Image 1 (cartoon, rainbow, N blue to C red):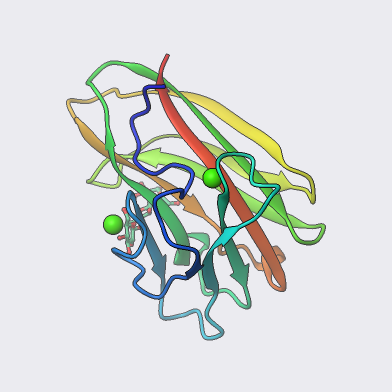
Image 2 (tube, helix red, strand yellow):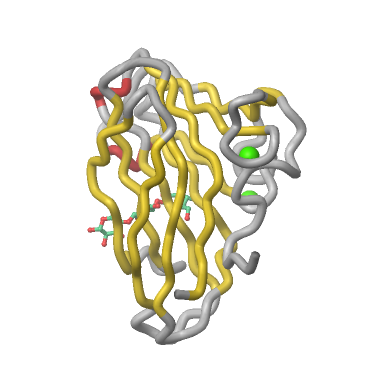
Length: 167
Ligand SMILES: OC[C@H]1O[C@@H](O[C@H]2[C@H](O)[C@@H](O)[C@H](O[C@H]3[C@H](O)[C@@H](O)[C@H](O)O[C@@H]3CO)O[C@@H]2CO)[C@H](O)[C@@H](O)[C@@H]1O
Ligand SMILES: [Ca+2]
Ligand SMILES: [Ca+2]
């Protein structure tokens, strides 16, 4: 497969809790804003029900901040070509009912090309997909996933298999 993003299924990362948020996970940048006073736990988990490979990323939300982007996992770099249309696909599920996530893609200037907004995440793995076009002259973009929704407090959201593919 040809994908724009790196380590989209976390298979390069050792299992364990991630505390180097910017660089602990190849291909991703994790962020927690300081308004989040009960910080989340980001963990790469080895599990037999990983949709891809043997590992997933688990995000346990113990609290939230002021905006959903105050807890994020962002794929970066994401290598693309100006004017090309891409398919985004990812897999997600949650430990408990009632989780919400937005899956977005944007450039280094934080201009957003597209998103799937307040997706309802269930306890079963589901694919989440949308198309976007690189409508400017950027070649290296990013794919922020927002987890900091109040409804997620006390839940764990699992993601795997991000693939951004030249349509
Ligand atoms: O690339 C990782 C960095 O992300 C920074 O947060 C950005 C979010 O990832 C992005 O979703 C958000 O996008 C804004 C957009 O700029 C605005 O036009 C639109 O109206 O709202 C979107 C969000 O709902 O931009 C922010 C940056 O302001 C982090 O701040 C950072 O820690 C991280 O490295
Ligand atoms: Ca995986
Ligand atoms: Ca990084």
